[PDB]
Image (cartoon, coloured by chain):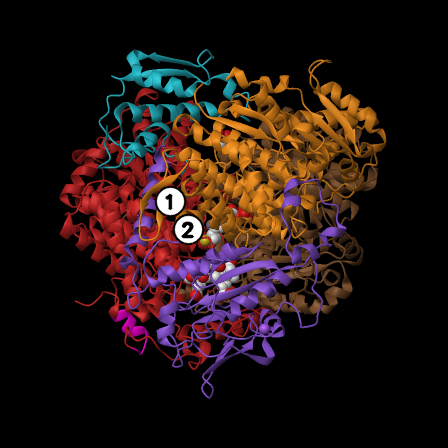
Chain colours: A brown, B red, C purple, D orange, E cyan
Amino acid sequence: ADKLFINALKKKFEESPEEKKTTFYTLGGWKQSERKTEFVNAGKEVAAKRGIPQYNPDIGTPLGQRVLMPYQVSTTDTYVEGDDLHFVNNAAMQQMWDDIRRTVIVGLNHAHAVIEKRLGKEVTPETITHYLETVNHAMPGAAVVQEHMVETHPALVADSYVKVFTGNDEIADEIDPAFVIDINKQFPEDQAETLKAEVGDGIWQVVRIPTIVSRTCDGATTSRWSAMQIGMSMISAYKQAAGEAATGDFAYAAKHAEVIHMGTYLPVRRARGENEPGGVPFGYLADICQSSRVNYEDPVRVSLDVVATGAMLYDQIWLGSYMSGGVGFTQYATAAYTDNILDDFTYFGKEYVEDKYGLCEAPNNMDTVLDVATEVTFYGLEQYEEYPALLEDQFGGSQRAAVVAAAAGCSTAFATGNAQTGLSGWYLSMYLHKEQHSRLGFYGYDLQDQCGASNVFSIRGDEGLPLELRGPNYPNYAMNVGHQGEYAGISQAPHAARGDAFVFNPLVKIAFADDNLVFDFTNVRGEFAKGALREFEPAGERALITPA
Amino acid sequence: ADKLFINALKKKFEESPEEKKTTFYTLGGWKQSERKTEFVNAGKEVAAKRGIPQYNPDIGTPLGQRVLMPYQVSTTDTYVEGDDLHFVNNAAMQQMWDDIRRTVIVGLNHAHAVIEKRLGKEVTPETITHYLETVNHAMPGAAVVQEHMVETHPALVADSYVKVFTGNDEIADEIDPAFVIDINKQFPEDQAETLKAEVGDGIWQVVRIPTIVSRTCDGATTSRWSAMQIGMSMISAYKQAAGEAATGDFAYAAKHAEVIHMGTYLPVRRARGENEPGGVPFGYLADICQSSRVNYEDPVRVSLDVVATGAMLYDQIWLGSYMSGGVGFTQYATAAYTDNILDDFTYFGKEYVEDKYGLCEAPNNMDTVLDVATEVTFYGLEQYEEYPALLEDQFGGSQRAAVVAAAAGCSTAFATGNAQTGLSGWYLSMYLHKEQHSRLGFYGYDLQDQCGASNVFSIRGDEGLPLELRGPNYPNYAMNVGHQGEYAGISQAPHAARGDAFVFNPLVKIAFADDNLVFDFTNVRGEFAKGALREFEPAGERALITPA
Amino acid sequence: AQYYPGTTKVAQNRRNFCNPEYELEKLREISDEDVVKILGHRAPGEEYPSVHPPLEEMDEPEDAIREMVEPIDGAKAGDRVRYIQFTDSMYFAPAQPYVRSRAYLCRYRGADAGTLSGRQIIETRERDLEKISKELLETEFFDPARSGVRGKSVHGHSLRLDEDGMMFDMLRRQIYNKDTGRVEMVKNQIGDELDEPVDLGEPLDEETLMEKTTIYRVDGEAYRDDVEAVEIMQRIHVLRSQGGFNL
Amino acid sequence: AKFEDKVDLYDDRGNLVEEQVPLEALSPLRNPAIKSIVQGIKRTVAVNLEGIENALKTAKVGGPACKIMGRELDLDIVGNAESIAAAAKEMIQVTEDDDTNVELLGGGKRALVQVPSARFDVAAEYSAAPLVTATAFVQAIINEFDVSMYDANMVKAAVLGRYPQSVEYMGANIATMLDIPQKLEGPGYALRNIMVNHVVAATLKNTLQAAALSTILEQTAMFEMGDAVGAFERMHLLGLAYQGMNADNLVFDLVKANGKEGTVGSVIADLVERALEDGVIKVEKELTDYKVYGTDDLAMWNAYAAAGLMAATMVNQGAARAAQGVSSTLLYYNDLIEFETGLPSVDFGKVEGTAVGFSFFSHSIYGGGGPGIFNGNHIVTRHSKGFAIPCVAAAMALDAGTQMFSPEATSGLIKEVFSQVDEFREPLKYVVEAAAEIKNEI
Amino acid sequence: KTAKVGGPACKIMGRELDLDIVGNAESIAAAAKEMIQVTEDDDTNVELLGGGKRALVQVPSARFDVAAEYSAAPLVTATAFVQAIINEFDVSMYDANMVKAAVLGRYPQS
Ligand code: F43
Ligand SMILES: C[C@@H](OP(=O)(O)O)[C@H](NC(=O)CCCCCCS)C(=O)O
Ligand SMILES: O=S(=O)(O)CCS
Ligand SMILES: O=S(=O)(O)CCS
Ligand code: NA
Ligand SMILES: [Zn+2]
């Protein structure tokens, strides 16, 4: 009936969403908020304990002259203060990143060829199972060969393990199911058929190293840690000399020749090793999100779960901490996953496309871009004009620009079945938005959006790239909030509409279809809400080795 | 009278330290050990809870056919099993790294020049104090300008703050003492005078960002997080426009023009940003350790406290996790800070030098290197031959090579007062050791030690460098255990003997003379022991925001 | 060739091990079949696996070096490259790690030798490995108490001996028989049980270990007391140091 | 005229080509053939037209296992290779009569491209070769089939991969012997980041040619790095001559004398005899039944020892027809020669050091791999200044098929294309010829 | 003179070397040029400025004709001046590494 955001707006304000006027200044400042009151009290205790002033509401300007809003986490009935969605205050958000950072995919195909060709030994579903029992002892940090080894405490590293998957059902059947990511169990029939065809008779490990290690160290640790314990377990299970020439072949295969990192390394100005957020391409992020395999009948839900995944990771943790820090960028991101606002805009666009073209049935050209992106942009902007509560909610121009353009781009991609024309729609939305309201985002919001139109279909060296392959290190995109997570959504959009099992990498898609992960990637926004309520239990805590 | 390691050997074994024979195989394997028994039970619980096999003492070969030893943490009376000194199992070791990783030093000279010359405003100790109260609200992640900001929970980020120091005593006295690192309080008279002369009228910030952020993100986050909140506090405290042209100068000053990183970024093959262990030069590591300012009358104690600091960080965390992983390199490192073994060897060398030359009174030449390094090497190796229990204790050749050469190199530096001839002694020790026992270390232990002699005094592009400037990224040193922490000790050695306040950077030395740090850098080995006993309370825990 | 400086028995023993014209003393008799069993790379009577075709069946490039360098028999046949690995007790074992690798590359063709503190390894074509391994097991390269054939779990070189004077072995691949005073190999080098144990003969007595050993020790001959050997090592250090600075 | 040294130059059959050649006629700074080889390697690119076509047909672009469903393009690229290559050359060339070369190979499945030297005369480095070639072929393919604005970005992905999201050309279907400048371990390292397998591929497993090309590249890098400046120049030039150029037929003759039954140890004995015979070393001191050798020319001793090192590798790894033991030869040749003579080993211990780590990182769990994947820019094998890697190239050339990561596996594209260039395939022949040409110009 | 080498605020106490470099700049520059040049008549340029406080160096183009990139310029220049300064004052093997640090900094650790 209502727009999907009406309940949220009603929960925020005393006024009806349509009302143009309100009352300020008499709300008690920070005292209106349970959370800010908790912070003020905490700041006093912290300062006293350590002998240095810390949090103090009297420093600078006085928060809370307007209503400090609750936010509904989209698709949930959970309403929380915005502070509960700051990544520092939300264990679910921290664990989502840890679960990606500590994952690598490592093939066994080169390794098995070394065993059979160089060593002259046999590989069977039986030897593989033995290897897997060995590596699941070894991977968390325990010994298999040497005498007088000291080891990691198993309870501190309980979240570390190794599983395998293959497209060959019979071989998968022969391996102990405790070690197997069952593609036929986790995916719907047509999707499972596609993924098994992509993988074929290949056998791949999904390695997850301990969260406590990932937090002590960095992302570039993951593929190295993985390789060391794969190496030990190959020695143990296949009876090599513990350190012969063939051992080097296994190292090179596991570290280089058949490894899939979640993120590639970054240039010097933003120097980082592998498996950091900036190296994760938009296509991978879409495939890490598991909404595709549970919500496949709803392409909007799938696309917007990917937007939530990316907005949090790319804006809050990556741009808001790795690349800057401080108070950071919580609400730049929450705009994309709260109050069912982006949902309303994107369901509108989906229905528009569905009624006019049919999904994936529009011509893949500029005519379609001009049609869909313009229509959806005008809808979104009209909602801010008709509902003053909505405009006061998403108060920053950057936040409105991202949300409107995300709906416009996803909807264009719903029509064409192609992410590149979806991207063209995103940029057109920005241009129309700017002229309509004589504003867009913050000072430097549209660096990429002004370069945008010309670089969508460019083929030049550092300009030309399918959107799925782009990411936070694509030059235009390397700096600014309110884009990266939304691009991940646009990457997902045409594939969700087409019913594709994956966006860019099928191995990555399968790798996170794993019930033994700590974070539930099938319900990203549900997890964010759980973290906001302080009900999420992360891995990597040191409680076992510290005083009571 | 007794060798310093004798009590430890008596605690480990029933036999007298000199006895050549013992009994094996009848100790019950892992069942002899309280810690391994804890691990076996924890592995059962972990596997049962998650549905995947994990720690299993019966995988591979059966640990504990010999005595699984307790280790005495050197200079303490604490005996623990080696597993308690694994960095994953030791919160003190993790917090030591976090305290280094989350620190930057940022000048206020430039910044104050911009305020006076470009904004045309005055800077006084009163304005600096107002700025410091502001930035100590802001740095942990709280707002000072915008309305409707969400913030970090003050209790989660209680370990984050900003202090300043200056060589000008009268100005330091005028800034509120809660924010000042008092050089005259923390350092002995002569050292205080040296450090204050080095800093002069300069004013420097020591910024520490939250441990929870450092663990969620990486080292390269630190100087960025620092700069954002320095920037906000400059705006607030000095009444800028919140975002004018001058704001860019403060950004460039805080991020580039006057920032001192703990570690510099690393090349692509071991790609990492700033403030990771590989970028920390040996001279900085010696200066981070605060033994110099408390144990200034015992140069051996100072040098070996630095070796403990470096062995743990460089071998256990850096080489043993960042650069590899798994069970890792606990005992490669513990050889340098347990059982008072390196202490015995190094006190011998110091007494030898003191008795023959006088500390820092030997000619700085090859004759002194040949004399001291040879004498000390022969002493150390004789102890392994005289005491079978000692040889069984430090069972790996790499561990003996590092310990013997560390004593030889430190002693040579005690004699010459110059780290470079100390380094030459280290390499000579290796060559003698190799010929004496027809073995040295592991397969690839002496890559750097064979290149060593020729590269000590080389002046060529990627070869020549004073030892103080060398670090984990010096090409020869980039790969292997049993060197880097010891080199940090040799860097400290001549300066400890000379009574120097610092080894390489006075700002780094002062920056860690701060009682508000979580880890106690004045007693590194005591802290390791506290962590081993599970008595250390780290920062960065998520208990406040998770289920009870 | 002079091989090594020094005037001790240790120094002479090191020279002897390296000198291909010095005939190693044979201490024990081991069958061809039992060498294959100890190696554990194939069963007795199993054909050598190949890693590539015979050289005579491949079209090798025109290459003067290929013409001048005669391939070992295992290379001609295309054998796998396999290994044998030894651990030597610091309590006066006859051979020691660097002594082995130096000697191997003086005595044997087509050899990949590796030195570590607790183990020493040679890798070469399988059928040639078997020939070399006979010599390594039968001669004074090996003592069945103070030395061990170990492909993994090598811990022991630095450990105290047991009551029988045997070196520690986590997998106990060599067992001392108190009834014979002889050592039997009960497992192959990777630790899998042998169908029938291999007689390795008696351990050398204390006096003979002293005569034959290549390790310097204070309770034997100390390295610091072989001044000519020490002098050459110090010379190497100085000349390397000067050379790195200038020429 | 800077140095007085002269060498005799031979071919790879051991025949004298040119006697009494001034040492500096072999310098990278002077020798026009070395200049031509270096400038050739900077400007040469292999293009896999078949790979591009298959990537497009399947939408498998941007790295391992990557695929974008719905983006498939069926283009007859190999079938129209002649027209596409001609169109590409028109964009790559500066003028119609310059040194641009574009040649189809494998029936059009592959292309050899040599970007004109004029483009490098006004370039800071070498990346113009892949980047100019990539965009010329992307544009040529788009123009050939009139690929729409909407689909053209797929052709770009098929050619150059995930760049610029990735720093490298991840998933690219072009290849060069050099890698991107960002991957340098230090300034001046670019000619060192050429995989050993690439060198062996380019020289078609001819042992002496592989050793030569490797030495030319390594020692030329030593000049760019500044290591061969001033005090050390002569040592580096003598190393190039004796280890890589077979000067005075020393390597060839040591191999001939020890090939039938020899070992590393017997090669050492012969080399020490030869050095003594030629007056390079003399007995400095007599100990107890032990002669301590000295020298008045450490650079020449180093050169002789380096030639022995190369010969010992060819004898030891040649006998095994298996490359893995080269790490052992590099270690123990140098370890043994020091205790045999009382003189420092090759590169004053640095070859031995490199060999220790190289052995470890080719027989352990921690990294590295087989001999063929190393190079002078690898963290494991960068430490010796030009004296270690040439032996690894020789060893891999002699390998009969024991390696999993062989040149066939890692360098197939390099082999087909770069081996077509005569001066890459037979570098020794050309450098010797050029040195004779400029003989009385030095 | 101050042993302040290797980056901002960095200093190694006890490593000070008192060398009259600017006073002997002409001799040092001539020695450096001899190492930087390939031949005598080539396009190498070494010119003193500011009374010997500064030097303009142009490394001969022949070095770049056989180089992959451009780093030969700072690296060749640095080592020529390091060697020239060492030779000028007969700096000992033990102290020469300080001259290297003063010219090129903390490379290669950085
Ligand atoms: C498989 C290798 C080859 C390789 O790449 N790495 C190994 C194994 C690896 C594993 C052993 C864990 C396990 O048992 O599952 C780890 C812990 C690294 C990891 N993956 O976490 C390790 N070595 Ni190792 N490794 C060590 C050592 C050594 C010594 C042991 C000599 C002895 O007599 O016991 C020798 C080298 C030498 O001879 O010098 C050695 C060899 C080897 N090292 C041989 C196995 C030897 C064997 O078969 O028993 N390590 C040491 O010398 C001390 C420290 C110790 C490390 C663990 C720690 O620091 O606590 C460990 C460090
Ligand atoms: C050599 C290199 O490995 P790669 O050959 O690149 O795979 C390197 N490893 C290491 O140096 C690991 C060092 C610590 C483990 C060995 C300690 S002795 C690295 O991962 O960058
Ligand atoms: O005001 S600015 O656009 O510079 C920053 C927005 S957070
Ligand atoms: O045996 S190796 O020297 O390769 C590894 C020692 S941990
Ligand atoms: Na017989
Ligand atoms: Zn971290």
The residue carrying mark 1 is B452
Asked if one can make out residue C212 in the rendered structure from this viewpoint, the answer is yes
Q: Residues within 10 Å of mark 1 (few under 14, many from 20)?
A: many
Residue D167 lies in quadrant: top right
Q: Label 1 amino acid?
A: Gly
The CA distance from mark 2 to mark 1 is 9 Å
Q: Return the residue at label 2.
A: B446
Q: Residue at x 33, y 28 (%)?
A: B111
> Which element type, helix, strand or loop, lies under badge 1?
helix
Q: Is residue A150 above or below residue D101?
A: below
Is residue B523 left or right of A210 when viewed as pictured? Answer: left
Q: Which residues are magenta?
A: B7-15
| Residue C214 location (% of width, % of height) | 39, 63
Disc 2 secondary structure class? loop
Q: Is residue B153 magenta?
A: no
Q: Is residue C44 above or below residue B210?
A: below
Q: Chain of mark 2?
A: B
Q: Residue at x 55, y 64 (%)?
A: C84
Residues at circles 2 and 1 in contact by the CB criterion of under 8 Å: yes
Looking at numbered disc 2 in the image, what kind of residue is underneath it?
A: Asp
